[PDB]
Image (cartoon, rainbow, N blue to C red; front, side, top):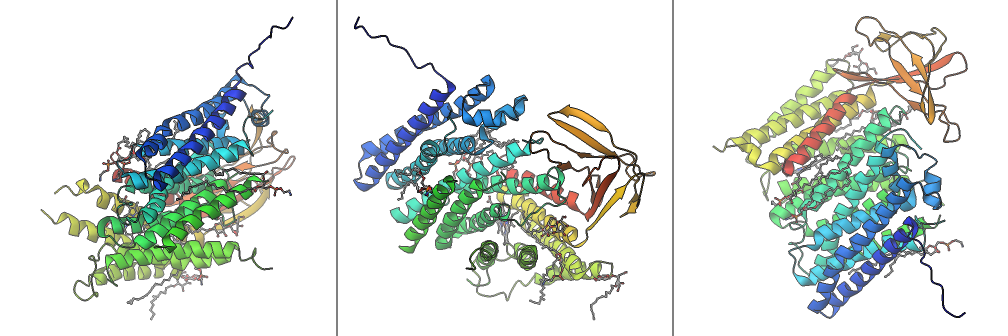
Length: 589
Ligand SMILES: CCCCCCCCCCCCCCCCCCCC(=O)O[C@H](COC(=O)CCCCCCCCCCCCCC)COP(=O)(O)OCCN
Ligand SMILES: CCCCCCCCCCCCCCCCCCCC(=O)O[C@H](COC(=O)CCCCCCCCCCCCCC)COP(=O)(O)OCCN
Ligand SMILES: CCCCCCCCCCCCCCCCCCCC(=O)O[C@H](COC(=O)CCCCCCCCCCCCCC)COP(=O)(O)OCCN
Ligand SMILES: CCCCCCCCCCCCCCCCCCCC(=O)O[C@H](COC(=O)CCCCCCCCCCCCCC)COP(=O)(O)OCCN
Ligand code: HEM
Ligand SMILES: CCCCCCCCCCCCO[C@@H]1O[C@H](CO)[C@@H](O[C@H]2O[C@H](CO)[C@@H](O)[C@H](O)[C@H]2O)[C@H](O)[C@H]1O
Ligand SMILES: CCCCCCCCCCCCO[C@@H]1O[C@H](CO)[C@@H](O[C@H]2O[C@H](CO)[C@@H](O)[C@H](O)[C@H]2O)[C@H](O)[C@H]1O
């Protein structure tokens, strides 16, 4: 005897993914080390090395993600993540969106999109001092994700019915990694002492990151109204408005970046806003719609904010700059009030607060958005071209045009604000196209105008739906109450339908002539979760309107109903569509 008998360890998805996250951690660790030596002692052979490791770090990250997709497709049940997330396992589209379903797979997809964005920024045309430092901080973020994926929270150990629970996560993860690369440049810029050049080289990641943020927030609104179906587009609970804080700051930052992009002004506020917006997007992406991983993310957040504002610490009035800076102050003040209100029950040792703070601040940004671009750059005082009458005229028109109907001073003043805003969009377009010719060539101005108008339409829609909504909860056998809000319904039974994993039950209703005839709102005894009854609502859109139909409890042989009535919520989503087809127009169609 005495001749050894070797075996392989057979190549699982498990050890492919383990070599994936470990090899990615190794590549990103030595990328952070070679980038830091490249800044400190100034040698070119280390800025070559950190730029050499961007492609292998992303490749090992892709190996780990494709190992998780591999395991989810081959129906290996030995790993903990797949055995706990193939308790919703069968269809093809949900097996490909299970690799970010719970926590560990989602931080794998998060670190993957980080590595992809670092790869796409690694071919930078950037001078080597802050090239070494952007690689240092971006490899640090990758090292945090794969460290927090490797020592804690590993995917490779041993629920619903809608697709937006797939695509609302990635929309923010993309958004975060977009706001990664300006922040990197900023923490580079304040250390490389070149304070203006950083934001005009990084501008498209800032716009695209904010576009992914705005599509995420509007998509979460639509999904919470129509598919999660608790009769509302917005929640002020500490999970939901925590994805409202980053979107606010990434908006203020977008406007300040544009100012210095065109003027070299507020580089101080730009550094502040990209640091605050980036760490905000971190803590918003960690705590979206869903132990000791929270401590690691809290330490990472503290590190990010402390680093950016520490390096900023070591380093006109009535104009378009003043209007944009006051608007960015309004955005930052709004995020400040939402954070200061969220922790105001925490730090002592509701929805009326947030609504009553949001309506004046929303009125202020909807006013400033109209008045700002109609101002010239760096003016002393508003004495010459006071065009502000006709805007005020439109403003005044809308208020009386609403006040001479039912509309309360909130709703009628919001009508005045939208009419003032469409007036400003026309005044901007008229004073733009008068140069004579295709104004559509100037993609920033015309796409921004479409985007500005789209928010204008949402301010009207939100104030009209917030003011004018009625809910009624009834219980009908073949009727108890029939007319609510313009159409009379009646009860016609329950059906049972089996489509799968969930059994569905029905309330079939009836309406006359052009009232929506025979509708069918839904309910699930959904077997997978602790036998709960969640609803999915049915809703007719109308020419002025949206009508939401709810089940509440379907009882044993008689059932209940809820019907809520809101105005202009469909026009809120046509405004969301207008924002999508405008921010795409800032890019190339
Ligand atoms: C010019 C600017 C350039 C700057 C670029 C540099 C960037 C560097 C990268 C930044 C990363 C920041 C990471 C800070 C987070 C640390 C937070 C610690 C978390 C923690 O202690 O968790 C506890 C222990 O868990 C545990 O059991 C241990 C968990 C440890 C997780 C750590 C994850 C590793 C992340 C990699 C960090 C980077 C390393 C540096 C190369 C909780 O549990 P408990 O004990 O309280 O339970 C209670 C029972 N009593
Ligand atoms: C319903 C599902 C929802 C899924 C949403 C998917 C989003 C659609 C993606 C469309 C684009 C995909 C194909 C185009 C490939 C383009 C890659 C290069 C992009 C690029 O070069 O842009 C740089 C910026 O990068 C950037 O700003 C970031 C580029 C990243 C593109 C978006 C990545 C999406 C990844 C999602 C994968 C899952 C989809 C699988 C079906 C330019 O910068 P610059 O240097 O020129 O600026 C200089 C300033 N002076
Ligand atoms: C699946 C759901 C996703 C919905 C998206 C709907 C539209 C899908 C297709 C988008 C195609 C847009 C054009 C893609 C071109 C990719 C090729 C790269 C070309 C390139 O590098 O040019 C850049 C354009 O930005 C870019 O690279 C554009 C990247 C494309 C992603 C942009 C979408 C994010 C914003 C819209 C939000 C809606 C998302 C809804 C989920 C920079 O320009 P430059 O070099 O000329 O700069 C200097 C001037 N000074
Ligand atoms: C200088 C030369 C002289 C010119 C003259 C100067 C005149 C200045 C005029 C400017 C005055 C600004 C006044 C703004 C008041 C807010 C009106 C809208 C409020 C509203 O929505 O209706 C409320 C009820 O809505 C509700 O119950 C829930 C509302 C939820 C908040 C609404 C969110 C709106 C956000 C809009 C989004 C904008 C786009 C964001 C990107 C009314 O109820 P109330 O009377 O009880 O209120 C009392 C709070 N103290
Ligand atoms: C605080 C009030 C606001 C003011 C004064 C304002 C002003 C401006 C200005 C001057 C521009 C440059 C193009 C132009 O001159 O039209 C611009 C661009 C833009 N704005 Fe606004 N804005 C405001 C609020 C908002 C809001 C609420 C949104 C969100 C819908 C928004 C989204 C955008 C976008 C996406 C661009 C294009 C930026 C680019 O990629 O170049 N702004 N804004
Ligand atoms: C482009 C992005 C811009 C986004 C702008 C949005 C900022 C302002 C947010 C306004 C919306 C807040 O609206 C919020 O809606 C929810 C859900 O409908 C309301 O919640 C409501 O739901 C229940 C449902 O039973 C009702 O019985 C109850 O009377 C009421 O509280 C909140 O009380 C209100 O605060
Ligand atoms: C010198 C003053 C200058 C300001 C000019 C104001 C113009 C005058 C506008 C008054 C017209 C509004 O008239 C009003 O209309 C509708 C029609 O049913 C009803 O509507 C009323 O209901 C609600 C009840 O909460 C009020 O909040 C609302 O503001 C009001 O419009 C009132 O019964 C009637 O008083």
